[PDB]
Length: 115
Ligand SMILES: *[C@@H]1O[C@H](CO)[C@@H](O)[C@H](O)[C@H]1NC(C)=O
Image 1 (cartoon, rainbow, N blue to C red):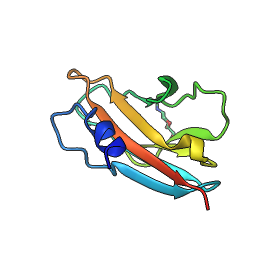
Image 2: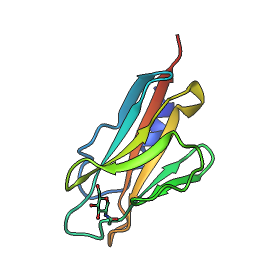
Image 3: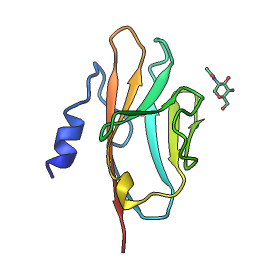
């Protein structure tokens, strides 16, 4: 597209993004955004909704008051942002930012489809 392209252009990293960069889901179903954490760097990650600049989570803790969001540790190097019930209003760009020395940013586009 170009919505998705402009979102991926916000990626700032030395290493190629090893997690999915495009997530399509059907509305009212769970979505899962994965972020790969450099294991020789400050392991702190925050999720950011680009549309309104909302800081959703900033590590193991949630900042948004929409209870459909949760952050979890899937593996030693992979964090998951769980969107419990995706709506058409949830489609758009999301940023995983790592407080490593180089300020690594990864970009994930969520597209929710409503039948
Ligand atoms: C993140 O959550 C896990 C549980 O999955 C916990 O074991 C770990 O200590 C937490 N880490 C931080 C940095 O808060």
